[PDB]
Amino acid sequence: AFLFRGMFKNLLKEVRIYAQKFIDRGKDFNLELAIKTRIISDGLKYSLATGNWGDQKKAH
Amino acid sequence: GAPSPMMPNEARLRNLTYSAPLYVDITKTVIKEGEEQLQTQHQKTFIGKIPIMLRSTYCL
Amino acid sequence: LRRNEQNGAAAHVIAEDVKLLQFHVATMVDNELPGLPRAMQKSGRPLK
DNA sequence: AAGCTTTATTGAGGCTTAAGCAGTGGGTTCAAGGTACTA
DNA sequence: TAGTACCTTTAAGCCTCAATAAAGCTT
RNA sequence: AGGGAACCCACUA
């Protein structure tokens, strides 16, 4: 759950970044295409595979 | 692209990650100046794969 | 830095590029200076 | 006169450097996704 | 118009500040 | 007739 809080926060961050980039252009966004499903997937997979409990860029 | 029920032994042999898909509901409401709201239902959007602990409730 | 000197630029730009050159030389010699970022690669592992 | 002013001691804060030897073995990730642009 | 190549943990030392005090300069 | 590095973990005396 400690992992998943950060990764769901990053999912919502990338959804807001995508949708912000697609409303500054005055368009509509595809929400099913807005979700970066690999944030939760490879984040959980990385932390369970390596054992480092965090993100890839903060291994130390 | 066809989903099949992955057994843990097949995950061990084929070097797969024994993970289950996570689906969430998002309701999109659009508020526009001088306009009403529209509530659109994206039911069960994929947002990632949760690794499953063996012999837990959502193990096979 | 040499290009920004020959294609002459601001003193602020040259100051920042001298600062980056100083950081790069110093981290090529020592990558453990406190109060300073580590010279990490794109993957995040610090350089030796 | 008693005030003024200058060069040698103290006390606390900041920086730096160190933290056993020799072996196996495995596991992961490095090197990664947007792009700007063509024949 | 689809597609491929490129852009970006603590423990002991040393050093260096602020703060003082006889002692000579100037009332 | 011999093309890996780094880190992590577990272990041995």
Image (spheres, coloured by chain):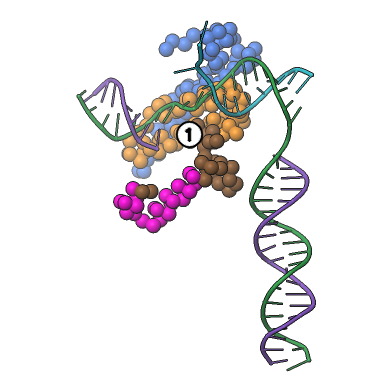
Chain colours: A orange, B blue, C brown, D green, E purple, F cyan
Comparing C4 with A60, the one in front is: C4
With C18 as the anchor, is B19 left or right in this view?
Answer: right
Could you tell me which residue is drawn at 56 percent across and 42 percent down?
C30
In x, y percent, where is residue B45?
Answer: 46, 23
Q: Quadrant of the C terminus of chain B?
A: top right
Query: Would residue B25 be visible to someone looking at this image?
Result: no
- The residue labelled by disc 1 is C42
Q: Main secondary structure of the magenta part?
A: helix
Question: Is B32 drawn above or below residue E1 in the view shown?
Answer: below
Could you tell me which residue is drawn at 42 percent across and 49 percent down?
C17
Could you tell me which residue is drawn at 40 percent across and 33 percent down?
B38
Asked where in the image residue D37 lies, by quadrant, the reply is top left
Comparing A3 with F6, the one in front is: F6
Asked where in the image residue D39 lies, by quadrant, the reply is top left
Q: Quadrant of the N terminus of chain B?
A: top left
With E7 as the anchor, is A57 left or right in this view?
Answer: right
Query: Would residue B56 be visible to someone looking at this image?
Result: yes
Could you tell me which residue is drawn at 39 percent across and 53 percent down?
C13
Comparing B58 with B29, the one in front is: B58
Q: Give the residue type that dot 1 points to.
A: Lys
Comparing A50 with A41, the one in front is: A50
- How packed mark 1 is, by other alpha carbons closer than 10 Å (few <14, some 14-19, many 20 or more), is few
Q: Is residue B25 magenta?
A: no
In x, y percent, where is residue C2?
Answer: 36, 48
